[PDB]
Image: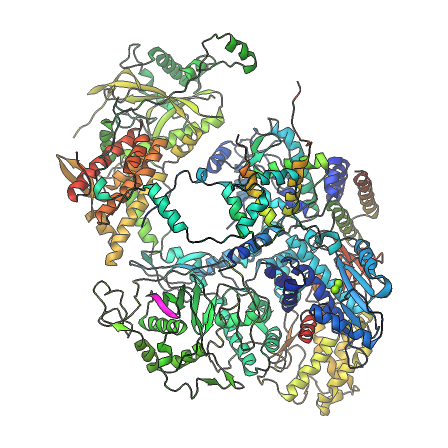
Amino acid sequence: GEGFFKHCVMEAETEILKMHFSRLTEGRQTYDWTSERNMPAATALQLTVDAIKETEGPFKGTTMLEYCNKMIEMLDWKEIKFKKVKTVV
Amino acid sequence: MSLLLTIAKEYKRLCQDAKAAQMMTVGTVSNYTTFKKWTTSRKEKNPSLRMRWAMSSKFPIIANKRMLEEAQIPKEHNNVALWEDTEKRDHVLASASCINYWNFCGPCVNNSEVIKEVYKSRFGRLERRKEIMWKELRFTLVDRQRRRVDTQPVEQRLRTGEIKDLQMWTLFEDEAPLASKFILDNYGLVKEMRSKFANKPLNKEVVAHMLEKQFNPESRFLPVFGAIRPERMELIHALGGETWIQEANTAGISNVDQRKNDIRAVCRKVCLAANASIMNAKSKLVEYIKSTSMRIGETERKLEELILETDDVSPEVTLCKSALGGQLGKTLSFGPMLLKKISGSGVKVKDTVYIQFEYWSEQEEFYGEYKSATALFSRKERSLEWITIGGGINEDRKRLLAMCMIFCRDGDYFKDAPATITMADLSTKLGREIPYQYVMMNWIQKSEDNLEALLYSRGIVETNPGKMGSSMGIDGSKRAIKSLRAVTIQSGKIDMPESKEKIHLELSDNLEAFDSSGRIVATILDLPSDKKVTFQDVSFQHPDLAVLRDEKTAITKGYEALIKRLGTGDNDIPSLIAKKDYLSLYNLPEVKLMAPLIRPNRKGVYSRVARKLVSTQVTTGHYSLHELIKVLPFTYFAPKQGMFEGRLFFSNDSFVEPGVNNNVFSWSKADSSKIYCHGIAIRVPLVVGDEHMDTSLALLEGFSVCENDPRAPMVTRQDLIDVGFGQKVRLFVGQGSVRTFKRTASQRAASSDVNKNVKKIK
Amino acid sequence: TFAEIAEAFLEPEAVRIAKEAVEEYGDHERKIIQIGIHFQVCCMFCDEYLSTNGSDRFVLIEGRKRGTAVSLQNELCKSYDLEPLPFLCDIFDREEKQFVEIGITRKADDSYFQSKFGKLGNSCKIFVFSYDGRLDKNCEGPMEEQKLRIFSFLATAADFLRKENMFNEIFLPDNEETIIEMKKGKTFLELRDESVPLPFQTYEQMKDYCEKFKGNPRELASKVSQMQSNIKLPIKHYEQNKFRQIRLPKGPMAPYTHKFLMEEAWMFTKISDPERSRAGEILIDFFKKGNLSAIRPKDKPLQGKYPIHYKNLWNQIKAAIADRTMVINENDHSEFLGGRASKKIPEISLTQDVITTEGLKQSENKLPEPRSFPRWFNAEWMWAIKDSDLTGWVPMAEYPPADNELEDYAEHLNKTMEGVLQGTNCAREMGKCILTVGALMTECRLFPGKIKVVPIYARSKERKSMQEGLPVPSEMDCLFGICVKSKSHDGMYTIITFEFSIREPNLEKHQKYTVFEAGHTTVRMKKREVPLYLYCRTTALSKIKNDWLSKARRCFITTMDTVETICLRESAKAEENLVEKTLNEKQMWIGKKNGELIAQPLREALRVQLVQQFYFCIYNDSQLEGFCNEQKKILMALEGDKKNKSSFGFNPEGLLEKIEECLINNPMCLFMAQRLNELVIEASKRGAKFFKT
Amino acid sequence: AVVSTHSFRTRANRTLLNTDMRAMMAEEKRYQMVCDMFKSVFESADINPPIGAMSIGEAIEEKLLERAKMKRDIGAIEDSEYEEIKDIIRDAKKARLES
Amino acid sequence: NITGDNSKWNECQQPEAYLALLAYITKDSSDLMKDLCSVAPVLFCNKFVK
Ligand SMILES: [Mg+2]
Ligand SMILES: [Mg+2]
């Protein structure tokens, strides 16, 4: 072809733009950085988002795009808040 | 009663917890789909081990307390503990053995019938196995490695989205979106399924999950051995593999397999209709499609929803789909042959040569599919570069060879000129010049010597040793004494490629689809079958096929006026029935249209008994809403005390008895539809027929959405039947959103409204 | 596939207008569906209705071409002489003779209406619809039927959008169509702008070189220079056909890695009760009432590493058995596990002891000592191959009902094969493995962190075909020895094996084992009591190993397939039932005796494959894994030479180096190595594309 | 292919709960009871992914009201009991608003 | 024919090269998703390993 890439990308764009970010929980184990441990993707994403919520207010993106936009927004954040467990005797 | 209460109290408790409260308020309901996904049940690292570990302990399993309390003793017969009060979840723990005990001694009766038709899928896949014979032998089999062929086939198979709609409607009403497209058109299956499954509230989730499978042919990529019928697929493993074989199988098949072929013939004729008139091919075929109604073995279904959503893609079927918005790519049709493209590309170029012609100059490698014969070809610069045949029967191999040579288009294509200019050249279809590939094609399809001619047009050589098995004879043998050039047979079949792709583009004015910006997939007219045989098939609207008499069109259209025009509002049948006033009904202007067609001799004597039945049914809970239509037209005339039986109503010498479905009037049982000879019509919105109990919630709808202003009382769906016409009311829809409606004129011109405007703009 | 989406819910031809409009009017692939609504929304509104005159009530302007839509909007200036509006509206009424324009918004209506109203004021009849049924309008609303049908369409469309979850994308220009850009955080932009490979630093320059790329044919010369620099090895098989035979390690002879002893192991018969045996944990308790109680070893042991400990423990077992099969020890347990803990030190306090080095602080790791090819292995294989007097060990289930065609075959083949392989000693060991490792696997759940006495047993029924009516074929279970559990470390369990034997121990292979002189046991036959030795050791069991070793039956299957295939492939040639014939006639090369290559029929050389698979189960070390997974290359090169396919291998020294590398101290691994040597040899002798030293 | 006469849940090990991982899981359980609650209200929730431009709580409230009215009008449940349910609903709406 | 197996397949490949290749593919498609393609590699061009 001559538009091989253009079209393949089209298909990609379509599927992704549709996608609800909850489907991101589907997959292998990934690194939760809140507790700095490995987790099943679902629980790790739960913490990630929950943290975003407690830092700056609940997430209303409902899409992979707005998720990604928030991701890039957090790099500029000077301060971030976590759900971290500290036991006291 | 407290079942609904304790839920409310729970909600109170949960919304008091601010943390849970805010997450419950913010956002759509769609969040549930995400929320559920934030819980895996448990760790899944070591499956078999975990289970072996699990059952090892005597009391691990989670179980249901309440029901067991109600029906049976919790204590044991051999004095080994079975029950405790110790717990977080409401479900209390118990031993494994108890389950076996209730199976043994539990008190229960009469569940047998309930079961099977829930899993008619599985149970049927059993039933089929009973009816077959057996035989045993061995061979070095050459199986057909890759066919994307339907397995586990079931009647009325459908797409995933639509089946989801069914799933919703049948399982429950309380939370279901009022989904139009599937329900209006495919109603009847809705009736059946909803009827058998809604009444006896059991296994609400499970049944749904298994119905999803019940209409889903698992079209996997599998190795077969010639038996390509979707029925032998289910149990291929027992039938064969590379060294196994079994016998006496073709016989027992579901009624689907032949029904699909019937639809192919349907599409054949429907396409011949558009072929007949070349004033337009686009605006006419679409009409023949949407008009035509199919009758499945147990259901009436539209032709549109069958075509758009059929699995098998035949040359005809391609054309049929092309009219609609149905993407079914990866398919290439040329005459009777089927092809797939696997390599390279090139542009369509024009080349006049002495016998204008379209030739392709691509180094393209494609796959050849013909009856009982498969092959691989590659063309470069309008001539076949590489060729290999994996066919079974010699003849079919030769056919392959030929057809593919045609598509190939060498210089020898031009050399052979017996006739053509006389007949094949110009096609007698409003003076339309038929395309040239298809011309020589038809020339070869004509006679036996025409095959021999171009078969000889290829270079012939005495093949070398080492090509003894590979070489192809003119007659189609493997002798290799004399053989064709640029061709070698393969001892065995040839694999078929597959691509998960969807492509669609409009069609040209001569039944040509230049899909994917070219590619000539449409093949014009595949097969010139001039035959007109049909069984239990409906057609409509100046079909150009004469099945419509003058007297029968008078009767039928006369009925259609009444049936069709009545439903919208006041002074139409529904409102009249609700008022219990049957006079206005008699005096209806659409009945007057029907008056003059009745037999004059007994006109009053008929009207007598007619006016009787209609009046007797006026009391509610006794009227048959079908019968009323059948009886009404005769009532118009003044009722004379005939005292002579009026069972046979001569409407221009043809009778219409009460009940007793006949030629003129078919009173179908258990679903809303009625046949008038070779034609069918039905009205959906106001049928409360006594028999339509299960879908008196579904069927009553002719409503639509307006505005949300009136604080219309939140009525339940069952309460919707009572609110009369022109009444704006409020209702809960689907899984959250609440909207408002009134008794409406149904949605109209879904397609045409746009289509005509689009035609006007040009 | 936006067309796929639009055409699925919208009207087929209605989409075509969107697709065309998107090429010129704007340029966004997704937005088709957005306008796909609006467009259709209009047509339904304006078609069914006609004026009192012959002409239609409304005329559509939106769907048309732009430049044409202008001049057609100028027609209204001629017809009705109203102010020529700058903004091109959608539809023109003729009964009302006024401008009509339709808007559709997801959110609360006011939000968008105030926008469009700001654009055109009262100059046009502006009608704005929400999908939900929210309504906002100019002064007069459309006729009562068209309202109903349009809202009905919009609501259903909405539900299809929610099912595909496309929402924020759909919003109208002023609201969200503008903000379709990817968010650009300075952090990110910087990271990107120094993530680039090329001499170019700014991303933009990298972008340009990419987008404006057209490669010339200089990669031919780039490839030839790459080739000259490559000096890539063009290798031939005839040249390296030697493969330096196969390298093998030199040192102490490898030991008995299997958790249990096979060949030398000794049995103790007991005729089982269905209700007594059922416990399986009481088996030994009922055994002890027999002769077992008598046996006691001397303090002075042959070839023993920790005599007194093992002797004491034996006494602790024997004593336990009388009362209950548990070892009542809190402290002896800890040592016995140890035969140890390492007390830990905080880094924080450690800094001073680095400054003041004490306790001799250092760091080292250790490696395993290489061993040499075993001799005993051959004898073990030869013993496992032959049939035992006891009939069957592995509990196999019943057979299913049969139809003539296929089932008769399967059922027959299975009954025959099971018949052969159940009699073998290999099967014996499979049995004891399964039953005992099963017993432990239960004991880990039953009493964790506890010390328990578990038997080493296997179940068998004896079969008698003397053709006489005997009392019965003998139904029983026999014992190999006693075993001790110790839970430690979740992780690997520590286990202590005690096996009876009648054979004199060999220091070379039983190095891990600690032997005693136990006593004398009676052995007899008729058509003599030999001294009894007690073998003791300790070993490590991973829960994983417990699992995979428990399910030893699996080995049967991998044999089966391997066997069966041969019979079909053969028979499939002659298209005849040659299974029965092939099993008995087809000859498989099994061994060498007196320097002569031997072969046995497939039915008895079946035992070989079975044993081979059983060993694969037992002797599985990461070593073995690597061995086979590199050995395959050897085998493929071999058959390459067989059918004269003129093979080649690029760096055989490297291959043989990896093969060597994975050969450490694994009896099986090495055994197979040496046997592959002999293969290479005899093969070289048949047809020469190999070496012999 | 799934057959239905025996279907049961395997109890999770007492390992993840003892560690601090449970102190984290205190959030996940708050998701659970909600999901369980909504599913008790809407039957097809798991089967059909719930849709519509509504909050979860709002749909829950209105649906509860519909089921209450249904059971009252024709079914066997008292009127003062229906009003008691209405009271619980509105009282729940207060706590919902405050957040 | 040759049976080809590769060693250290991942170690050799570089996200730096993937960034460029992704920029080549997304050259024409869209400037709204091109920027969403280029982001994935740069997080591996600047990656930290525990
Ligand atoms: Mg406009
Ligand atoms: Mg507009």
Task: Tell me the quarter of the picture where residue B562 sits.
Answer: bottom right
Q: Residue at x 76, y 36 (%)?
A: B18
Q: Main secondary structure of the magenta part?
A: strand
Q: List x then y, in percent, for residue E46.
A: 55, 36
Q: Nearer the viewer, residue B715 or C227?
A: C227
In reply to whether residue B384 is colored magenta, the answer given is yes
Q: Nearer the viewer, residue D6 or B452?
A: B452
Q: Residue at x 34, y 70 (%)?
A: B397
Q: List x then y, in percent, for residue A37.
A: 57, 30
Pick the quarter of the image with the N terminus of chain B: top right
Task: Tell me the quarter of the picture where residue B627 sits.
Answer: bottom right
Which quarter holds ligand 1?
bottom right
Task: Tell me the quarter of the picture where residue A72 sits.
Answer: top right
Residue segment shown in magenta? B381-386
Which residue is farthest bottom?
B601
Instruction: Say left or right for B715 vs B232.
Output: right
Above or below residue A52? Residue B305 is below
Q: List x then y, in percent, for residue C574.
A: 23, 58
Above or below residue B102? Residue B109 is below
Above or below residue A80? Residue B35 is below
